[PDB]
Length: 257
Ligand SMILES: [Zn+2]
Image 1 (cartoon, rainbow, N blue to C red):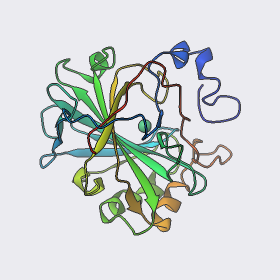
Image 2: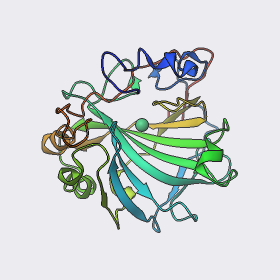
Image 3: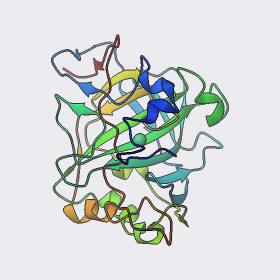
């Protein structure tokens, strides 16, 4: 039912998902004047050498690259996190134009896109159990700006033509998610939610300060995808981002000075 249209987009999600009006919704604007450096925050640790990508899928709202999360092959630890979080999928949100597309903003600035690397806490034993808990998920969010090409993104861009419409998928093995990281892993963190329905308040957000650069050619490939299924009227998969939600009572902490 839900999507990003005038009729079914973020403004309306609360009708079927009333947590959309909740106290810990994502994304948020990150005000660098109030998001204070916290010298107790630890560095992020990613152990991705055994990461095992399986498939890439157009699910009608984005494309997901899915990973084998049956063992500790690709894990996020440290930062604000207690214990071990396994990578299950990554996906992006992006705009129709370069000046919009990110979900998080930084002093109201919107980036061209935002990458989300979705991990779940092995405390809970599978993703479905994890999403029911406040400490269930950790999502690493990485901004994209348009400039030089990102070499590590090219493998993704090169298969998007094979999953144009909703429901299409392709084999996608041997993808290295380290290739999507920026050089600095300085971050902001706060407690929040999934940014699509069901909007569950189960996420420790970790949003990197440093954007990655992608080329105009790369992000243009994103914008050729379709929200629709095969044989339906074309609706380009663009502006699949939720806008900033109220911070309410929450604290955003910065890992860096
Ligand atoms: Zn996302």
